[PDB]
Amino acid sequence: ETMGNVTTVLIRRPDLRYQLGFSVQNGIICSLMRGGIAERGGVRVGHRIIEINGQSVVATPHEKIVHILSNAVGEIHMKTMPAA
Image (tube, rainbow, N blue to C red; front, top):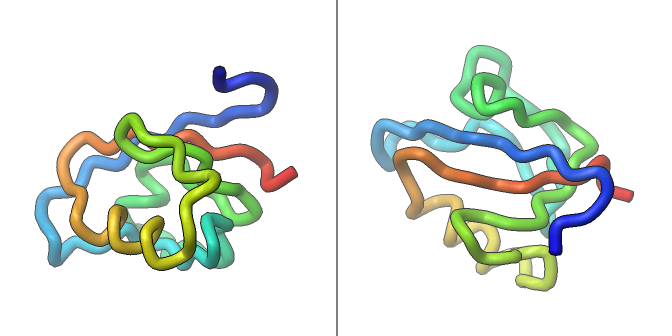
């Protein structure tokens, strides 16, 4: 599993008030807040989140993907691809 163009991201989130800092739609990063944790994480726009903290969310719906990101803090391992 995890083949090809995968760019793992580590988000280190202090708590829930420190939101990701990137706008995602359906798992695809649409925008990134510069200076935010996501930038520090290595998140880039035009990337598709394929996994979050050990669960492949690439087949996970919008809500779920967002709900999961919204509640996860600490060292967060995501796997992103160039949305291809």
